[PDB]
Amino acid sequence: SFSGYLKLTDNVYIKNADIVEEAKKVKPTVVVNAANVYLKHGGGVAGALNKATNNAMQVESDDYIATNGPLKVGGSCVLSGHNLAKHCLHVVGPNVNKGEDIQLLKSAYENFNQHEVLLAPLLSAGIFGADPIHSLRVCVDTVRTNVYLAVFDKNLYDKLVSSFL
Ligand SMILES: Nc1cnc2n[nH]cc2c1
Image 1: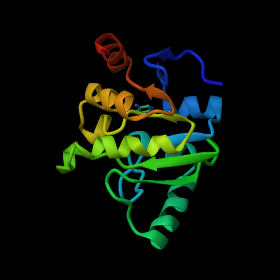
Image 2: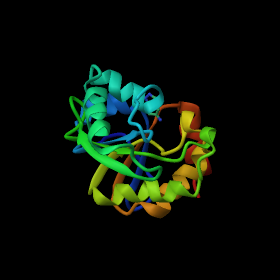
Image 3: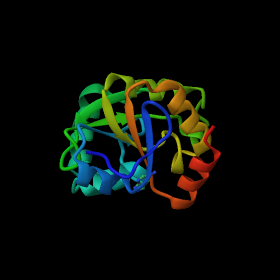
């Protein structure tokens, strides 16, 4: 199971870790991807997870988009987890660098409540442009299921833990 996590609340845990490396080690039932509406896994967590699947995640995603069209900002879809997890929950947090409504971050986190336990990154953090301290606050106040947060950057991890109310 998950190891080396700091408990933040009854159901939220956090660790300074590469989510690709965490997923390969634990092989969780669900790994969350920081997806965009087109499931174009170019950079950030999405690019890293996709590269770990040898592009199989992108091939599957393109077939999903061809059939279903794009996701909504705040929405999600469950696809295969490939070599990383049983499933990948592709969740679209608002991208602040695209002028997307930050209030959609709570809607994005609500998707996590459909899964008993998840390995996840902070939604809308990193290249999505939102304040990661705000993302962690929305996470703890929205997610009721067990969420194991992987924060890649050590310096951001320390800031998140030390400022956690
Ligand atoms: N917050 C995270 C977690 N794992 C990551 N792997 N590559 C980029 C990442 C960002």
